[PDB]
Amino acid sequence: LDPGLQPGQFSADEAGAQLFAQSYQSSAEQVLFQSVAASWAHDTNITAENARRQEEAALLSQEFAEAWGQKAKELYEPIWQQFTDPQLRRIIGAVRTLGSANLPLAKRQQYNALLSQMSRIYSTAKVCLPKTATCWSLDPDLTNILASSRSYAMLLFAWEGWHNAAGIPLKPLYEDFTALSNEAYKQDGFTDTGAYWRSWYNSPTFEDDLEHLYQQLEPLYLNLHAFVRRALHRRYGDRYINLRGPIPAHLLGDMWAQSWENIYDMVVPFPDKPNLDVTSTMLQQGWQATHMFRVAEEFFTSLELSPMPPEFWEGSMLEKPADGREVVCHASAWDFYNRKDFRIKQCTRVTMDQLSTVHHEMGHIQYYLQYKDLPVSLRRGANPGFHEAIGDVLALSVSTPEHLHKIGLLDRVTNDTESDINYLLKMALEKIAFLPFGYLVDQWRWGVFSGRTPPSRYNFDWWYLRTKYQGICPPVTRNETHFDAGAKFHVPNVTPYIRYFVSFVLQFQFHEALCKEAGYEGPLHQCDIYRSTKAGAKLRKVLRAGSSRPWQEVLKDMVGLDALDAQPLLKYFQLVTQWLQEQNQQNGEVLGWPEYQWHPPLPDNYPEGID
Ligand SMILES: *[C@@H]1O[C@H](CO[C@@H]2O[C@@H](C)[C@@H](O)[C@@H](O)[C@@H]2O)[C@@H](O[C@@H]2O[C@H](CO)[C@@H](O[C@@H]3O[C@H](CO)[C@@H](O)[C@H](O)[C@@H]3O)[C@H](O)[C@H]2NC(C)=O)[C@H](O)[C@H]1NC(C)=O
Ligand SMILES: CCCC[C@H](N[C@@H](CCc1ccccc1)C(=O)O)C(=O)N[C@@H](Cc1ccc(O)cc1)C(=O)O
Ligand SMILES: *[C@@H]1O[C@H](CO[C@@H]2O[C@@H](C)[C@@H](O)[C@@H](O)[C@@H]2O)[C@@H](O)[C@H](O)[C@H]1NC(C)=O
Ligand SMILES: *[C@@H]1O[C@H](CO)[C@@H](O)[C@H](O)[C@H]1NC(C)=O
Ligand SMILES: [Cl-]
Ligand SMILES: [Mg+2]
Ligand SMILES: [Zn+2]
Image 1 (cartoon, rainbow, N blue to C red):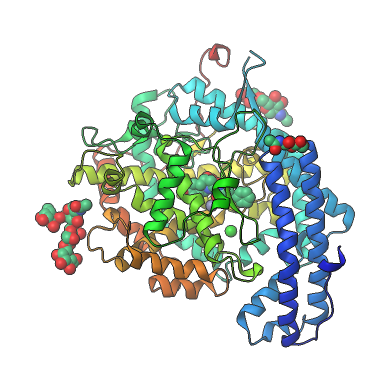
Image 2 (cartoon, protein in one colour):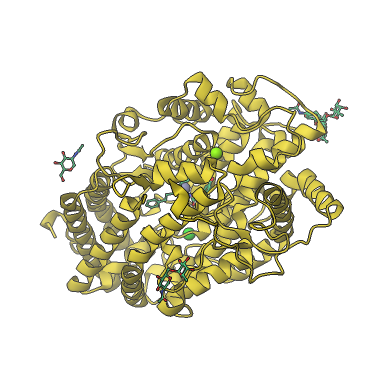
């Protein structure tokens, strides 16, 4: 570790901890920047040499973390919990958590290599056609197939091809990662890595609180599921759709069946009302990636939040490179921890759902811009779910028919009950369909980290959860050679997921509060906070707090409640919740999937007829 980056000496008291945190911040920003920059160079240009440099940067970060972590525990282990300065407690508490820096050097190198290799496998996996040369990438190729194809056999080829190509090679690496991760965090005092991940929410009742939320939300999902299953039955037939069983997992518009907005055209209750999927208009009008990011930016500035700085436009990767070089296409927003460089890396496609993704990612950037002057350790969301909700909340306003009209994406304006059902159904396909998936992913991973799910049951327990919560089934047979959890980005890239369940609840609490602050006095689902500087100032207070204060208190200040609450989501959706319940009763639907063992047959002449 460079001498200038090494911890000096400080008193064993709070006043020494304060000087300790300032000296830490100085060197931490440099160590973080080199690490983030190395990751950027790799993720925008996947090569063996760039992976080598990223692993070296990661090792330097662990060296820094160990030196300052062990100094913090040498001086302040018994006194940090009683500091008068609450923010200093939070800084010290972070510095003393060593994580992977607890591993001996050889195991640190093994850990870093596993992360690099798992990331490379996921982001370079291809589905090749039997033209053995011609191969499809996840983004854009397979994504577009899952979204736009209505051929059962083609969707099956993409789904199976992807899950086999990405998942199978990941499994042995993921087992080794799990063990090393647990070994590291057990030395921080946690029973397993999942216990450390859950500790970020600082709630002893976290898992019970989540379960109580899901109980309130499940009836909405069950009714949406049944309605969509009926629509799929009308298209695909009784051979491929069981009206009393799970839905085949490749028919819902998305590789993970996690959002169903891409099948809206098949389920739209009132098709002679305005077409709320504006993708065709974006195409017809010549929208490009840069337009989408500028439109998102202008929403933020309309609230008197910050525009994207020049460094963002100069540094960001907003389209998949055409030079063919391999990149991580999965969208992400980057803080370089130097208070200057902030970037998005997105293989942007011109679609309405991608416009939502742009807002999501710009939400992350806006957070970074607002807390850039806090101590580096507090440059975080109040909890990780706050960070995920910011851009989604703005996108709730952007997607309203009234707002789409303002930005020239929807000429026809209507305010009637049928148009409301259409819109709320489209929003339910995006938001309510996700809830079971957002809930289940880390239930699977918590079980893996705790040892309840050993490698011999990775796929068994994955599909148990997928059927239990989402009510879907794999469209081809799977066994424990398959590792279908690994075919979802966040698993090999070791990104926790419960934040997204939290953020899908929170964003409606936020929306309700901002709409009220904006002076809006109509239905919650028609609110548009565009150009509300009052709403912007309330949101700005959250963003500037970072993780300096307990999230329960930040939430109370914003929305008047100190807890996650499903009521605002329920209130947003109430008209379509009622409508879907009535429609399923009239149609005699069975809610749920009592034929839990059912799987669709293979197409005749599959995969042979894929050409
Ligand atoms: C779409 O239309 C709805 C419904 O509009 C209402 O019902 C129609 C059948 C007609 O009779 C309309 O004349 C009638 O307004 C609109 O929602 C409604 O908005 C109004 C105005 O913001 C709300 O009235 C306000 O109520 C608050 C108290 O809640 C008072 O303080 C205000 O002074 C004002 O009277 C009304 O409550 C609201 N209705 C519901 C059920 O929420 C909606 O604004 C409109 N949307 C668009 C984009 O035009
Ligand atoms: C719309 C955003 C899609 C892209 C997003 N990308 C991650 C990168 C996280 C990351 C962390 C550390 C290193 C690298 C990446 C991020 O921005 O959170 C993502 O995955 N969202 C979830 C979940 C989700 C789905 C719909 C939403 O409206 C919001 C969230 C999903 O699509 O499954
Ligand atoms: C796991 O499955 C692999 C792929 O074949 C699968 O099972 C057959 C019966 C078909 O249903 C097919 O659609 C499935 O994808 C096998 O090659 C492999 O041997 C199996 N692994 C073990 C350990 O048995
Ligand atoms: C990709 O990385 C290599 C080093 O592995 C470098 O020589 C090359 O210039 C990079 N390409 C781009 C476009 O940055
Ligand atoms: Cl999280
Ligand atoms: Mg779409
Ligand atoms: Zn995010």
